[PDB]
Image (cartoon, rainbow, N blue to C red):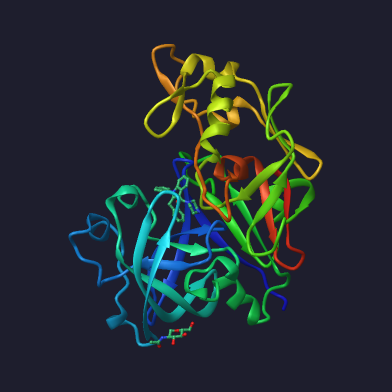
Length: 337
Ligand SMILES: O=C(c1c(Cc2ccccc2)n(-c2ccccc2)c2ccccc12)N1CCNCC1
Ligand SMILES: *[C@@H]1O[C@H](CO)[C@@H](O)[C@H](O)[C@H]1NC(C)=O
């Protein structure tokens, strides 16, 4: 068609980027992450037991208040690297950036405190392919494309560096195109290894001058739902050894004074080198030799068939404006602004 639709995103602490969607008639509004690492839409349900503290602290969908709701009831379990949710399938009208679509989604009735008591968002909108959809439910972007309204069969992500500042724009998703106000130079495209997953070949990971990791190639999942850049436990422990970082419970840390002294990290993608300086990957909350500063990179062991794989999350997207091209099964990067 002839239209472009944008979704304004809120940036919470450079870790969570989410926007609003409306579900039902009248619309029930939810804060959702737009996740290229998954293919299902879900929100917490009014049928969720209140013994789940996450269901007490999040917005719940009430099918009994929606006149456009259509029952299904098929049970589903959605397993992620950080945790699992369980519930059942429902159908209703979903509003995303002015676009209205009839969508099958999950009503979550089992929502663990860890990690969901840490989510500022309520649910998730899966931006991945039908191949990875649980219960083979048609993903939302596929349903939007069927309407024949969007200018291009593409969607783009802008994640802002600034979270603290008001009047800044936390981020932005453009359905059906890109926003040239948020990137500079030209897009550099990398073809997907295969359709069904937003995953590309990575030809090397350099720490400083030498290529210390991913010699002989490896995989890179471009994941909008991930806060950090992640690699396997084996890759990260080698990376962190090179940086001189100390392993804590879930993350890696450096003495704050040493943060600025850290080397550049380069990701070799489609013949181009994508470089992050220490300012890009260190949470520089102070300069004290008496304080510990977290790194926006951690270990995450993603199981087969998708993994073992690196994941390029918000840490990477903040520097590089990303276009997800469904028409040509490729990913484009440009310097964000
Ligand atoms: O499990 C996670 C991730 C989730 C929770 C989630 C689940 C589904 C969609 C979006 C966010 N979060 C997460 C973010 C904030 C609070 C609690 C969890 C991560 C933070 C860093 C790395 C990974 C994940 N992912 C796997 C699936 N793709 C996105 C990343
Ligand atoms: C739920 O919807 C799916 C469509 O994917 C269909 O296969 C199934 O029969 C539906 N179940 C009910 C109980 O309506």
